[PDB]
Amino acid sequence: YFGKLESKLSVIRNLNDQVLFIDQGNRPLFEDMTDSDCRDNAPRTIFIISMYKDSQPRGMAVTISVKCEKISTLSCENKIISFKEMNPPDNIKDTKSDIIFFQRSVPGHDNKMQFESSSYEGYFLACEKERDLFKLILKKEDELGDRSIMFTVQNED
Image 1 (tube, rainbow, N blue to C red):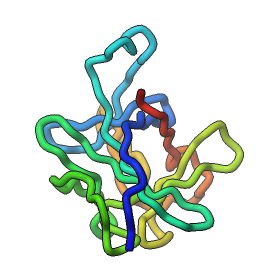
Image 2 (tube, rainbow, N blue to C red):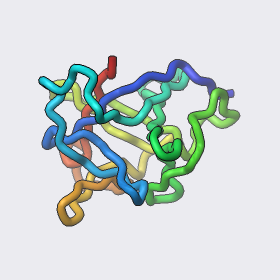
Image 3 (tube, rainbow, N blue to C red):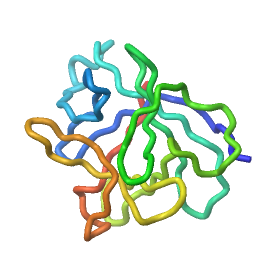
Image 4 (cartoon, one colour):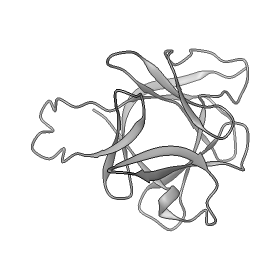
């Protein structure tokens, strides 16, 4: 069955150069981070990303998990996003879990990626502008090549 490849920290930036963050409501928002001068042991810390072993033609299986007040992993129930309090599994029976995510680089860009459902296509992760915060949900835009539904992932070390 499924399996864990390697767990490591990765910075998730948005289209406006915003780093994913969590709030008191365990909601995935987007904040601003320089990471230029404060990089030297910066207080803030992004969520953890666990890579799973998958032998697919094109598909990066990853899983985001926020650690601080309570470990919570990003899980997409049906069409909405929900944070499930639980550390990233070490070995899953199914190849596509509710927490598993399908990352796919975007063609014709620097290093953008697209978050797709573990099961199959139909719903892609995007960022919704709510009030003064950019939240993250699962929707189906009209254009798959729209930056609005594109995200950036970097290595944290």
